[PDB]
Amino acid sequence: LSPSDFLDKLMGRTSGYDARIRPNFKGPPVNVTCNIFINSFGSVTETTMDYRVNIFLRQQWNDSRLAYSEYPDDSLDLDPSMLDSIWKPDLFFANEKGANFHDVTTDNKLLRISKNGKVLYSIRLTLTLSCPMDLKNFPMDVQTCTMQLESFGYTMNDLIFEWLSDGPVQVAEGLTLPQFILKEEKELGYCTKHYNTGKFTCIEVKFHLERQMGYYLIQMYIPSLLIVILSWVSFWINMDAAPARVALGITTVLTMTTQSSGSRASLPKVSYVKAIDIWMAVCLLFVFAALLEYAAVNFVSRKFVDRAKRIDTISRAAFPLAFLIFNIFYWITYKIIRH
Amino acid sequence: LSPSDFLDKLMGRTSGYDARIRPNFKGPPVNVTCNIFINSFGSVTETTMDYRVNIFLRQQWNDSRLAYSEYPDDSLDLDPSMLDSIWKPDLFFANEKGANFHDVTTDNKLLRISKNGKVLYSIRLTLTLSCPMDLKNFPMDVQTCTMQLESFGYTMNDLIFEWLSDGPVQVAEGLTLPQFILKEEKELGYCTKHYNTGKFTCIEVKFHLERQMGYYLIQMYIPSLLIVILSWVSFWINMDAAPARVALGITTVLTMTTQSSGSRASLPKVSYVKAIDIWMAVCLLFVFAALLEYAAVNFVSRKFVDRAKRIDTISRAAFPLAFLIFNIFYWITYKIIRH
Amino acid sequence: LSPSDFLDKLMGRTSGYDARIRPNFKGPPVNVTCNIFINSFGSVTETTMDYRVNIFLRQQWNDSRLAYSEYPDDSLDLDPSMLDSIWKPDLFFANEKGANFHDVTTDNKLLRISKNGKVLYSIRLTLTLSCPMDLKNFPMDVQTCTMQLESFGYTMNDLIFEWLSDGPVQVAEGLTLPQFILKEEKELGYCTKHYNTGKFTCIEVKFHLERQMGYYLIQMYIPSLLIVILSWVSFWINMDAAPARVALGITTVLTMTTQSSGSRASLPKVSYVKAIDIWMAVCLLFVFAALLEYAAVNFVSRKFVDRAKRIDTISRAAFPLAFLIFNIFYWITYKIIRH
Amino acid sequence: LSPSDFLDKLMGRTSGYDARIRPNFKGPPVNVTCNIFINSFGSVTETTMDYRVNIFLRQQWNDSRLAYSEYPDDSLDLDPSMLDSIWKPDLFFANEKGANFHDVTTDNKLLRISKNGKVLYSIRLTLTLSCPMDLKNFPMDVQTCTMQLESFGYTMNDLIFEWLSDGPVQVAEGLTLPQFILKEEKELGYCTKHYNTGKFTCIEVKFHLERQMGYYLIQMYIPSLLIVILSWVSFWINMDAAPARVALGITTVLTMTTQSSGSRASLPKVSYVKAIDIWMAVCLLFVFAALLEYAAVNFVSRKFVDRAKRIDTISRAAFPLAFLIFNIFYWITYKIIRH
Amino acid sequence: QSAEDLARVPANSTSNILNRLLVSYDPRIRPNFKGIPVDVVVNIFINSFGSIQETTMDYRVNIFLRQKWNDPRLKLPSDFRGSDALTVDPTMYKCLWKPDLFFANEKSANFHDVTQENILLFIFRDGDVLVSMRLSITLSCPLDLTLFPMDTQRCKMQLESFGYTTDDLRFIWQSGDPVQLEKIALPQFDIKKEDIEYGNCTKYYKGTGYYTCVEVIFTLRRQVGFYMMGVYAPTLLIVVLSWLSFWINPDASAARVPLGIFSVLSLASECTTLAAELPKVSYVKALDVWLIACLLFGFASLVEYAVVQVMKRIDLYARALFPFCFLFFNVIYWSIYL
Ligand SMILES: O=C1C[C@@H]2OCC=C3CN4CC[C@]56c7ccccc7N1[C@H]5[C@H]2[C@H]3C[C@H]46
Ligand SMILES: O=C1C[C@@H]2OCC=C3CN4CC[C@]56c7ccccc7N1[C@H]5[C@H]2[C@H]3C[C@H]46
Ligand SMILES: O=C1C[C@@H]2OCC=C3CN4CC[C@]56c7ccccc7N1[C@H]5[C@H]2[C@H]3C[C@H]46
Ligand SMILES: O=C1C[C@@H]2OCC=C3CN4CC[C@]56c7ccccc7N1[C@H]5[C@H]2[C@H]3C[C@H]46
Ligand SMILES: O=C1C[C@@H]2OCC=C3CN4CC[C@]56c7ccccc7N1[C@H]5[C@H]2[C@H]3C[C@H]46
Ligand SMILES: *[C@@H]1O[C@H](CO)[C@@H](O)[C@H](O)[C@H]1NC(C)=O
Ligand SMILES: *[C@@H]1O[C@H](CO)[C@@H](O)[C@H](O)[C@H]1NC(C)=O
Ligand SMILES: *[C@@H]1O[C@H](CO)[C@@H](O)[C@H](O)[C@H]1NC(C)=O
Ligand SMILES: *[C@@H]1O[C@H](CO)[C@@H](O)[C@H](O)[C@H]1NC(C)=O
Ligand SMILES: *[C@@H]1O[C@H](CO)[C@@H](O)[C@H](O)[C@H]1NC(C)=O
Ligand SMILES: *[C@@H]1O[C@H](CO)[C@@H](O)[C@H](O)[C@H]1NC(C)=O
Ligand SMILES: *[C@@H]1O[C@H](CO)[C@@H](O)[C@H](O)[C@H]1NC(C)=O
Ligand SMILES: *[C@@H]1O[C@H](CO)[C@@H](O)[C@H](O)[C@H]1NC(C)=O
Ligand SMILES: *[C@@H]1O[C@H](CO)[C@@H](O)[C@H](O)[C@H]1NC(C)=O
């Protein structure tokens, strides 16, 4: 007969099947094998510590009550309307902020009952997970964005999740992010919570987002470094030309202050110190030291002009070595040591 | 004898009909023919890689069960409230990030049954699809933003989509985007996803979005180009002058730095080096090189004038030619060979 | 007796009435006299090309199937919950982007039936209507942001919308917009859709918006024009006293570049050339021209001094004429013609 | 028999359970031991004066009519669908702005009725809680954000809330706020809203949000100190150098005022004076005071020649004393006198 | 509807014999039908008042809209004494008539549904029905920020009837403390309970009746301290700097060059940097008048430098005239735009 009528003969109000009771009741816990297939991975914002995904969640399990060997069609499938007549594992995402199904042209979910009792459930969810990023070393950071599936009111001896055998988490092939790159090293583990009541089951997949810094290396480091070079060539050459020296000093400290405090609207607003902020502050300190050493040579000037030019030449030899020492001790620290 | 009660015997209780069984069941597939009519378009954002489109989507398919012969009216339609009494193909959008129908003054859903059996279904959706944008060459790039219709749990031996013959996707005429321009040539074809559970039918459209470049040409390229040309004009004057070239050199440097530091609030906040960042860094490097290779002349001058005169006579032809070879490289790399 | 059962004796199950058959079925079409009454207006956003308006909407039409002369109470009221029993004409705003009702403290609908069958249906909608804007001439422009009301499923052979005679579209008094000023001349018109199915009625209203340039005059026209006059006054000096003339030239070019930077920082994000960016590029070009005049005078001056004073006087007479010709052409083409 | 049918036997149309009246009606109050478990804590803004939290809220209360001793199950669960067939205490957050439940795969409510009468009701809410924060001492402020639960319908004659004994509010380990740092000392107490009808019960928990002044201290404070030092070094030189004093004076005034106006667009947009504004104004005032001291000692040089030198040597020891006195009167009143 | 009974004693049996099963209490027809107008007694209680967006002209506010009227068809019988306030649950909130008010200038209003529904209804002995409901409205008030850093915005909230004229429904305030509010902190403005001025204002909509209405008018005075210690005193300091730059010697020196080229550059880079922080509103605000005046004075300083070096006799007049010419403007501007 028809799959609808045979289905309601199998799982209706009659025939002894309560949806509100788990299969294998008073026995071994069910093994809900679930996997995800993510489509979009966007808006990894730093002002709210979240990221939005749009996944396909497919979970399979067993129940002896939905078994049959009398019907021609081997895998029945019920419409997404009457999904309240089958027990479903009551999972939820342990850290999601906002999340919702999709309802374009139909309900985007599916439930198939195989002949061997294997029940297959597939949803299309949109989630906004919460990942606690740290921007301590900002333009060279590596973030771990996690996603945890968990049960809601079923203990480990009542229900357990476990990932699929092969390919439990797989992204779409053509996705890309504005700032980060989603690496191909995702880690799949268990983080089972040991709460006050019992050990509620939970599984976790963590993605590694690695930030690329071409934009910052072009438009945040190089202008300030060239400004520092100009700050040195101020007093490297112009010995006696004081109006051709004070002007370069004013302009270089002014353009460095403008570069430092007019490029913070394009950086994520946090309050702890970032790497780019340390570098900006050290460049500001260096141009300040350039202007101060000019003023010191001018002070010691007004029988001693040889000592004045000697201090000038010693500073012109010491500033590049000092900046190379800082630059090395910064780059080997942030790029190779903390990575 | 009325179209309110004729349907209650055509597809209601006193009729053999199931809204969960496709026509021609266990036979040939159902050739659903779809076509779109794009009303609005926009919100193309580089931060979340999406774009919002407000479409009239219609799809037609003929079933042998919904055919009448005794009725006087050719095409009768039922209310959208009773849209759970006809099999409708689950047509979901394979790259959406959220969709919703429209229900102003009446729900915007229409289903009309013809006399031979041709069901027509026209709805109005407000999707926000996701096209991955790649801003490698930013002020001159195209964006192939797609739209992927697909079925959800009907393989290609059950359901098959295909476009109309004449004018599948016909965008409205009065469209005007803030950044892009929708090119009037919309590519259209099949994607036909082959998952590990069957071959699922699919049809897709690709729009080409080309940038408008005039605003960046007026406000980014041309002022910096005139700045670097004026910077060459600077060191073309006599060399025996302490404040007469430092002024124009540091003027060019200050204007270049404030230009490149004020333009960082109008670009898309991505973190890989694009075309405009390369062009804004190279001109800054050039005006810095002009100021530095004047300061070196002012150093080396104090027959000691002959070497500085040779340096000036070399540099006066070195800088414009080494700029107009890079200019050729840039405008054949970004405008020509990368299309 | 009471209204709540008189409606059951008029349109209910016992009497003859149908909830999806139009008045005068298979006869002359029904003429819906539609008018609106806006309350709010704003969010005219040029980055998504859509405004938002919060309207009352009154549609009145006659149907003799509700004509009654049974008891003298001549104003029947249906509650806004059993609103699916009467026939009400479908109406969808053919350019909306998302729009919905209001449901605070009650349902915000009303349906009053009169004696002669003329019923009056008033709803309170909020609408995010789409408006294709045009910022070719930004601070001096007009927007013809329109609004259409179209039938959905009923051709012009079955239903016809028409505006009310005595001021169909009204405006709540004291309505201020942050940018525009809504005119008192609103052009009501007969749109008409001629699609492949048939011809569908479509009434429309076109508001005119005028951007008031009072802020742009005080903040971006007067300072730049002042800087152009200052750049004139720079080389208006007679002798070759260097630091004053060089000071004023560098001053004017730095402040003009900073003005251009801030103008990009505050203005709309549109990637085609606007009539404010033309007028900023030209002022930047004129300050470039004055600096180049100084550089040329210095380059020719060490017979030579006579030609130097000659070209200085010629430029001092020619630059005001050039700027006046440009300003005349600019303000006639933007403030006068395209107005 | 089945636990669902046993719930139908225990409460329904068979027994005398009335789901609209409180337990032990016409008698003593019913204490509800409540405890929360926060999962996210973010979006704490200063523009709309509210934060956003994502909690697991749990309530335990005794119900006399829900005891039983003739069933093998030690504690039954209750379906989230048939959950409005029981008494539940109306508990709302008195300072919320937007609050919603979750259902990501199923409803996230869980109701467990014990064998003696204990009832556990656990839900998962997302809340936007309105806390009013002041920024009178901004970059070292400590904001107390409260969450106050209170009854809606019943007074304290009927319903009495109280927190749990051990660990009422817990925090999910690994939280990180963008610009704050949450302290582990949560001060929880009673609230007892005294209204006109009766004293409605009210409990509350106050988190102590502390801010961390890294980005502000490195981006603003240290540049301000350096510019004040440069202003001192300006007139620390002798009067033989007429250019250098006024040059460094204009230099320090400009970099101070542009650091102020560059910081002014990254602070929270409020209208009362913050603690950073007082510092960035007084530092500008002292830089201007040093430059006006230079103007005075140039105005008096028209005790024949030491009338300027004595005042300059007095300033060269009196301005650091003024800055030190301001620092001791600032870093005490903001860092230690407002705890 | 047709269910026989469930209980006889408690506060639900009286509702079952009061409406929807017993004698017809039609919830569609108002009390005193074709008699006198019903008198609804409203009094809001504000819990939150914020997000005054100067780009959309709105403000969000959370109220407790209590409304209490007199229904003689719900006269509680004298069978009991303990049911002085017969509390009906919101499952039957639609089975009794309720006045259909609405906010005539709202934008997107919605209820609250946390852990329960937030509507409480009481039915008293003498027939007085009371409805409290928590509400989260976002009304619209036309902000006119011409006097921007010193302006006072009045924003009003008006309750109205929807379909019931003045001879059918009529709103009156409680007449004792009708608009209360908690301690609330606006980010920029300053709400004050000293001005909470309210009143009736019915509208005469043409053709169809004369609809009732009440309204509250909050007054908000935007505090000025950040702007005064921000873009007022540093900008005035820049202008005073460029004035005092006339005291440097021109004779055989080159150090007035930076004090000019950086004064004008600093004032321009303050003006057009402020131009993004201000509310994006395209008409002349008082702050913009101040900024253009300060830029005119910097331009005047540099053109005075030009005229003294294109023509002792002019500097001594400029130093004593133009810093004295600032004061007249600084008096008339703060007298007009304040
Ligand atoms: O009492 C609680 C609160 C606590 O909330 C943190 C999250 C949890 C997730 N699951 C879902 C509900 C919960 C649970 C199950 C059975 C009784 C009490 C109970 N809970 C929450 C609890 C943990 C564990 C479990
Ligand atoms: O079991 C699955 C998982 C898999 O998820 C990736 C996306 C897919 C696209 N659609 C969505 C529903 C799905 C499907 C149909 C019938 C049985 C199982 C099933 N799903 C997904 C599947 C593919 C193919 C198909
Ligand atoms: O067959 C169609 C598709 C077409 O879609 C573009 C939008 C239109 C808007 N109105 C609403 C529905 C529609 C219509 C009415 C009756 C039969 C078919 C039908 N439509 C759409 C149509 C046009 C015209 C009309
Ligand atoms: O009469 C009132 C009005 C007043 O409104 C401010 C909000 C309050 C919150 N709770 C919820 C409803 C209320 C209440 C309960 C019982 C009778 C009357 C009544 N109210 C509101 C009241 C306060 C106190 C209480
Ligand atoms: O018939 C109408 C249309 C008209 O729309 C402009 C808005 C108005 C606001 N109030 C609320 C609804 C309205 C009204 C009440 C009762 C019957 C009809 C009716 N309306 C609108 C009306 C005015 C007056 C009134
Ligand atoms: C589920 O996992 C448990 C783990 O011990 C195992 O004993 C059982 O056989 C599995 N399969 C079921 C319950 O079908
Ligand atoms: C279900 O039962 C079958 C019985 O053979 C077993 O092989 C399978 O592992 C079980 N689990 C799933 C998820 O199919
Ligand atoms: C659908 O099209 C296919 C062609 O690929 C055809 O074989 C089949 O019969 C068609 N089915 C119907 C119902 O027209
Ligand atoms: C109707 O079905 C028949 C298949 O036998 C064919 O004429 C045609 O493809 C169908 N019409 C459609 C799809 O519009
Ligand atoms: C409606 O408008 C049409 C326009 O042609 C007119 O013929 C007709 O008389 C009008 N009235 C009715 C009731 O159809
Ligand atoms: C509807 O028909 C009646 C017939 O008496 C007429 O008086 C009325 O004006 C008509 N209404 C419209 C809107 O045409
Ligand atoms: C509830 O019942 C338990 C039963 O042991 C008792 O201990 C407790 O005091 C009661 N009250 C509360 C508030 O838990
Ligand atoms: C609730 O708390 C009160 C204390 O106010 C106590 O007297 C009572 O025993 C507790 N339990 C119940 C069930 O009322
Ligand atoms: C308040 O409302 C209107 C406003 O003019 C007025 O007619 C009425 O009498 C006033 N007083 C009341 C309702 O007590």
Image: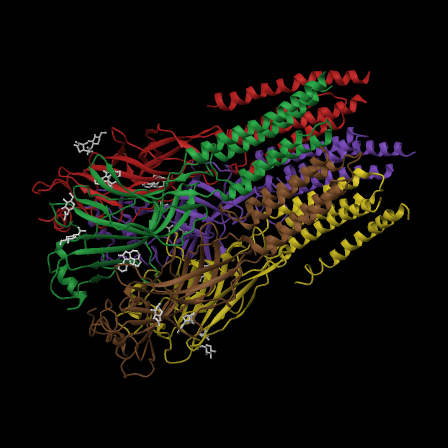
Chain colours: A purple, B red, C green, D yellow, E brown
User: Relative to the observer, which residue lies in front, E283 or B26?
Assistant: E283
Q: Residue at x 58, y 33 (%)?
A: A214
- Determine whether A148 is above or below E79 in the image: above
Apparent side of residue C276 relative to residue B51 in the rendered image (left or right): right
**Viewer-nearest residue: B70 or B20:** B70
The quadrant in which residue C282 appears is: top right
Residue nearest the observer in this picture, C235 or C169: C235
Image position, residue D120 (x, y; %): 42, 66
D93 in relation to C246, above or below: below
Residue lying furthest right in this view? A303
Q: Position of residue B111 (x, y in %)?
A: 21, 43
Provide residue A299's location: percent of width, then percent of height.
84, 39
* Residue at the far left in the pictured view: B70
Locate residue B190, reporting x and y percent. 32, 30
Q: Nearer the viewer, residue D139 or C232?
A: C232
Quick check: A292 left or right of D218? right
Is residue B227 visible to the viewer in this orientation of the structure? Answer: no
Vertical relation: B255 (above or below) D251:
above
In the image, ligand 9 is in what quadrant? top left
Q: Does the image show residue A114? A: yes
